[PDB]
Amino acid sequence: FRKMAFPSGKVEGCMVQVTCGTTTLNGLWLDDVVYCPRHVICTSEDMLNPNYEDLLIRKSNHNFLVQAGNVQLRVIGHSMQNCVLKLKVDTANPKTPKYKFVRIQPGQTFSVLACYNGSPSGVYQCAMRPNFTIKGSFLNGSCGSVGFNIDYDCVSFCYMAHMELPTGVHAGTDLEGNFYGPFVDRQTAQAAGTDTTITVNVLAWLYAAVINGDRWFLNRFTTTLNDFNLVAMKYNYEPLTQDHVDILGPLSAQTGIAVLDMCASLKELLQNGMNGRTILGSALLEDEFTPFDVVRQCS
Amino acid sequence: FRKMAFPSGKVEGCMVQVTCGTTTLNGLWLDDVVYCPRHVICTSEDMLNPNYEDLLIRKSNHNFLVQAGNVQLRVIGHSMQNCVLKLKVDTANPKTPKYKFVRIQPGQTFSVLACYNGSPSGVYQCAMRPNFTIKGSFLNGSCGSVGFNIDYDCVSFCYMAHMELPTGVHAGTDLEGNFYGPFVDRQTAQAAGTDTTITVNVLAWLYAAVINGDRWFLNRFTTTLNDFNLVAMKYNYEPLTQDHVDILGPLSAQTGIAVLDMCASLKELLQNGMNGRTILGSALLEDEFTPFDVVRQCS
Image 1 (tube, rainbow over the protein chains, first blue to last red):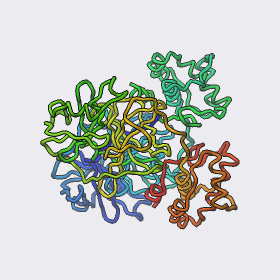
Image 2 (image 1 turned 90 degrees about the vertical axis):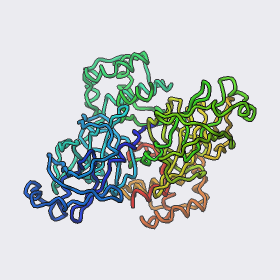
Image 3 (image 1 turned 135 degrees about the vertical axis):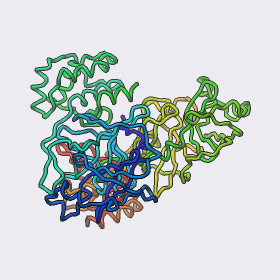
Image 4 (image 1 turned 60 degrees about the vertical axis):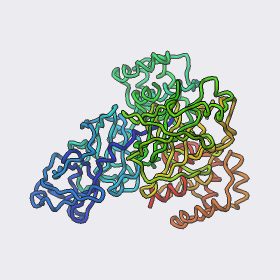
């Protein structure tokens, strides 16, 4: 069962390079505006306790060097929205796709175009962790890399990277400058809170194994939502809500397995173990597939 | 450690839909030639024992309908090279990237752009298994999907999918129509030989773990190349050759751990087992990262 990313062509046409002084990172060019992290007006000695509000007023438009491949963009205005910087240019991007800005919830999935230079270099599929961090790549320079979903022909941008934490994860904001989680863009000691497994996603991954003919883990028993969550808290699983149960309705119909029946299966795997056998080629339970992802891939 | 695919934009601009009678599948439009699997001239009847030379002789150019998005292309010639059909059109692809055709060997990695319609739908990173099959998509219609690498703005095409095997994996050809492995484009009882773990890739993935500060699996022992292969084959691992020892030279230099010392580490995980700990976030040893891949993401 391949974890697949969305094709990145529509986003590749929007990536630019933004340089201010000695620091360079990636920006997003849509219409006649370039979006990038605001801490580009900072150096390393400036990152300690910077006042972006006071620092930005001393900048001038030509202080910003923007290159779209081998062409230079003329900056004609600057402004700031939360933790995102907005550079206005004199030319609208002819490769601009149909797009919109959205904010996702913990547990939802999206694709990330990692640009560790100023030109794209790789793409991968990931999930927003309950502690609001993203694992992703480990080679940097990708500050300003973007995350997105695609629905037919419309790109929904949901994430832009700002910082890399000590454990290899990074943290960021939506495209309107609002951070995900309790992080800030300062040079302070920051650390991610303890993480948790995404219960509804693990259940959706078990429906996909049954659709692919992997049925050894099913049993005859059922459980209550209360009895299950008591199990969930002991193994560091997110509690299951009635909202999550409804989302799984379609897969329960297609397979003929009641949602609380699959919870019985999951209950035994956690309590008892996987006994050497594997589900879809993996000895661990996968939690980076949403219910929606499973149906999209299983028609 | 993200398994990353290459950005797919340059390949997306080359995907077309090819229809012949009742059969439709994906094609590759480069310059004024479209490449696709030759079994697009077959029915469900002809796939048992088709005579392609006889089926192609009965066709004329107007028998082939080629659609590039919202535009139909005019076919002005047809030809066959091994198991690949070549359609000549009167219009060159304006989005043709710098490209070339190559043939890979088992163990190498590449990206797959899955188009289960005539339009792209997902991208993923994979490795050619020692038994010559690919762990690919599971919803069909993707026949004619393409696999590629990108190095310095040049697209290297290495794979096109032709058939779906009974275990869910796919088999295919290079871009010159020659199959990988002992497979043919007939719908006869075919099966892949037993698979094996790609030893040299696992060793490169263990060097990457040491680069990220994960050293718990190391020990103070060394081994001979023969004693290692004696243990390795017992777990269905590929034998290690002196050429594979050389390939790992750079990574051993960067870390300061001799290749045969790392083989000792792997020997211990295999003989004794992993049990409860996980290495790079996996309770299984990973084999879809080549030495080349490791150096490109760990500098």
